[PDB]
Image (cartoon, rainbow, N blue to C red; front, top):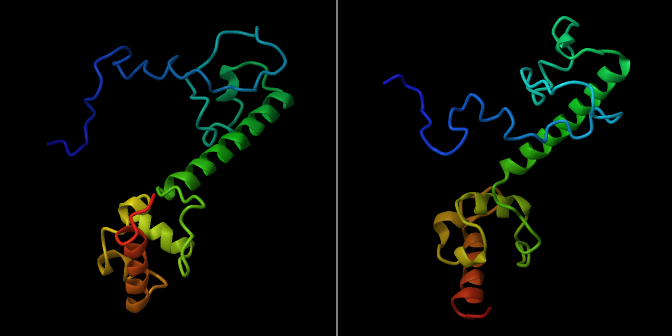
Length: 165
């Protein structure tokens, strides 16, 4: 009715969703206050995770944590660089939901993009590739009809006609 995909999943502790991220995921400031540990109570009302609308902000917003000197802003910039590297790695890993290992290029003619698109079709490993034919191995960027037929025939020979493991 409202048009929003609601969320009704969990009834267990911290189900309020208002404090479910307060102190349930505490590993956010890994190496930030590397001088010591007794300064004040932790401050969560800013997020500690965004680092985009928080890294370079005027002094009126970063005043919530006192001691906004040059070492503080430099450590904040370093933590921002690290978080940006982490989200870059997460983006590079979450795009290709195929997990291409070195066990995908043992044939003669297959390349990286072919294996990427083939596994992105909805399959994972050779155990679930010889069950199809031209219907998926064709129309790929770099494969014709005869090449796809020959490759799927080789797959059927190595899986259906050989029966080895």
